[PDB]
Image (cartoon, rainbow, N blue to C red):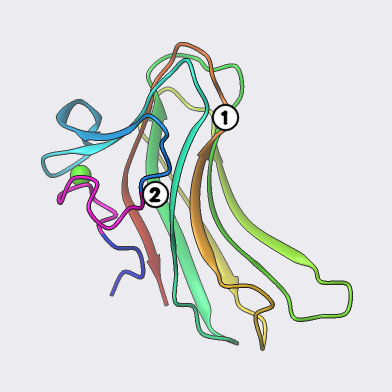
Amino acid sequence: SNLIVNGTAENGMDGWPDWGYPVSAVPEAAYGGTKGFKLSGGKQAGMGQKVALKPNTTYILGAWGKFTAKPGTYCDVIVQYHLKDANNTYVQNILRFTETDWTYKQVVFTTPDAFGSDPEFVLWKDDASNADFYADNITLVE
Ligand SMILES: [Ca+2]
């Protein structure tokens, strides 16, 4: 059971709030199925959704990703939340992609005993070079 809605782009951009960035669900970006997510070159771009994480629970976050040509910087896949501690610590669980062939990355993390902010998944492309980024099969599972 994937906590991310439509992590495969098989339902287009459905389940993903429009943040106004150049993110499309298109055949050229597919790792599998009929579509993948394409984050346009030339601009920073991201999308995300709130994720219903449980406390003291272990999760695996994974995704396939590639740039179409060598980028200036990177694109991150992140699950993030604040702790409910005195310092109000911000936790980012991050996969950082810079590669130009399809590359699978994953991170295993265990959630704290309480959240200080609503957990979110975020895909964020810092890079604004000419290369497009393709993301597909984005997965967050207990
Ligand atoms: Ca797909």
Which secondary structure lies at badge 2?
Answer: strand
Decide which of 36, 13 is in the foreground and name it: 13
Disc number for residue 13: none
Q: Is residue 76 above or below residue 142?
A: above
| Precedes in sequence: disc 1 or disc 2 | 2
**Residue at the spot 22% in from the left edge and 53% down from the top edge:** 14
The 10 Å Cα crowd at callout 2, few under 14, some 14 to 19, many 20 or more, is many
Residue of label 1 = 74
Quadrant housing residue 32: top left
**Residue at the spot 42% in from the left edge and 55% down from the top edge:** 62
The quadrant the N terminus occupies is bottom left
Q: Is residue 95 above or below residue 114?
A: above
Determine whether, in the image, residue 104 is placed left or right of residue 10.
right
Q: Position of residue 68 (x, y in %)?
A: 37, 18
Q: Is residue 54 above or below residue 15?
A: below
Determine whether, in the image, residue 38 is placed left or right of residue 74.
left
Disc number for residue 63: 2
Q: Position of residue 82 (x, y in %)?
A: 70, 70
- What's the amino acid at mark 1? Tyr
Which secondary structure lies at badge 1?
Answer: loop
Q: Position of residue 24 (x, y in %)?
A: 27, 34
Q: Is residue 110 above or below residue 128?
A: below
| Magenta span contains residue 118 | no
Quadrant housing residue 100: top left
| Magenta span contains residue 15 | yes
How many marks can you see?
A: 2
Determine whether, in the image, residue 132 is placed left or right of residue 14.
right
Q: Residue furthest top?
A: 130
> Disc 1 and disc 2: Cα gap in Å?
14 Å
Q: Which residues are magenta?
A: 6-17
